[PDB]
Amino acid sequence: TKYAEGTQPFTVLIEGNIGSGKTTYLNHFEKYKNDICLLTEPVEKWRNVNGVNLLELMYKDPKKWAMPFQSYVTLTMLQSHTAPTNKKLKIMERSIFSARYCFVENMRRNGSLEQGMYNTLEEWYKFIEESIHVQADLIIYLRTSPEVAYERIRQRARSEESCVPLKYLQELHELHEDWLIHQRRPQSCKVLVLDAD
Amino acid sequence: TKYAEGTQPFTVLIEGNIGSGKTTYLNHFEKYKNDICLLTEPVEKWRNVNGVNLLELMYKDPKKWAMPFQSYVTLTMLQSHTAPTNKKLKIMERSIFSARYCFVENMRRNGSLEQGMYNTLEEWYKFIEESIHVQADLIIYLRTSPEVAYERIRQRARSEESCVPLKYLQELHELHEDWLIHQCKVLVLDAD
């Protein structure tokens, strides 16, 4: 019954904090484009929604734009999770789960999402899980320490994420740990932890 | 492939402006509960989302709450449009379409939804149409004039929808007219 059910191959989700070197890690799979469906984080869509840069707006004014931004993230994630494909392996940078369990959760805690906004997002996630099929067979967790991650961001061209405080990266780190190490979260499927230092 | 495809009976959508007497019109179907799937507008859900009243918040502060509220409306509409059922006929108060074509569209125009917010909503609507099945066989349009509708709202039990200006109901009226008269089958009824 679920949308896109049984239309998806073996799927690997690349998880990790901001600045854990996910983009770098995924470049290594570039040359396998022919046999591997390789979907990077849809940052591009988020940067340009018919001209509006939601990502910049979210970072510049979280109390106003987190809700629409995250709602859009969720959608783009679903578009990735369900895009049809010939290939026998699929690899996604981040997932609907990291969006729900880390980023939205953290934006609730630091006041960016108000209860009414958070609840709306959660109702969507609840509906999505009952009615849309999300293939997830293996997660590769690029585990790093907040400080190493902070450093990596600092060594890169000024982006929109560049101003996030070390405090934010700590909050996010603990949330990934809760989900993928302390298994504190519905997620079922195997996690392969890699030390990215 | 689409979710809830071929799992839905003949469906009638009751459309009409706020205060066009849709609730009244639907009470007439009450006694047919046994053979008719009868789904009223999920106002109740919108009033209470784990304790948050999104409807009140939207009316009190549109620039802040329209986006989340409308996002929620869309979801509750999908929940209704896809709820499974035995019955051979289904009747829904309002629909995902009225939400998209009238209310969201109007909220864009009067500045309540900024372009970033509006586009987010539209992207969802686009996704929804390509991937979820929305059964709609007949629309009953309860057509009325803004003024009759406004008077109506005034008599009734003061809600959140009280404070609304006649200007708003005019905007909404024209939007329904554009959708339902000026380009499935529409059955127009004069509700005056």
Image: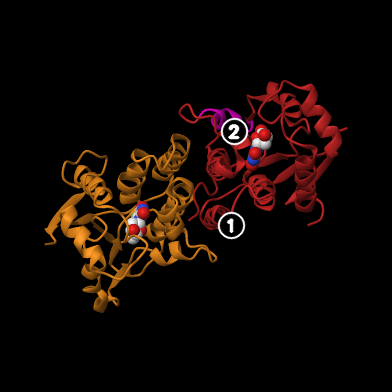
Chain colours: A orange, B red
In this picture, residue B190 sits left or right of residue B72: right
Q: Residue at x 54, y 29 (%)?
A: B53
Q: Chain of mark 2?
A: B
Q: Look at the image and say whether residue B46 sits in the magenta stretch.
A: yes
* Pointer 2 residue: B55
- Which comes sooner in the sequence, label 1 or label 2? 2
Task: Give the percent coordinates (x, y) of residue B19.
Answer: 76, 32
Q: Residue at x 25, y 76 (%)?
A: A32
Q: Residue at x 45, y 28 (%)?
A: B50
Is B160 above or below relative to B177?
Answer: above
- Out of A132 and A22, give the one closest to the viewer: A22
Q: Residues within 10 Å of mark 1 (few under 14, many from 20)?
A: some
Q: Which secondary structure, mark 1?
A: helix
Task: Give the percent coordinates (x, y) of residue B31.
Answer: 69, 21
- Magenta segment: B39-48
Q: Residues within 10 Å of mark 2 (few under 14, many from 20)?
A: many
Is A100 above or below relative to A59?
Answer: above
Under mark 1, the amino acid is Gln
Under mark 2, the amino acid is Leu
* Pointer 1 residue: B115
- Out of B85 and A13, give the one closest to the viewer: A13
Q: Look at the image and say whether residue B171 sits in the magenta stretch.
A: no
Task: Give the percent coordinates (x, y) of residue A164.
Answer: 31, 55
Task: Give the percent coordinates (x, y) of residue B183.
Answer: 78, 57
Q: Chain of mark 1?
A: B
In this picture, residue A142 sits left or right of residue B107: left
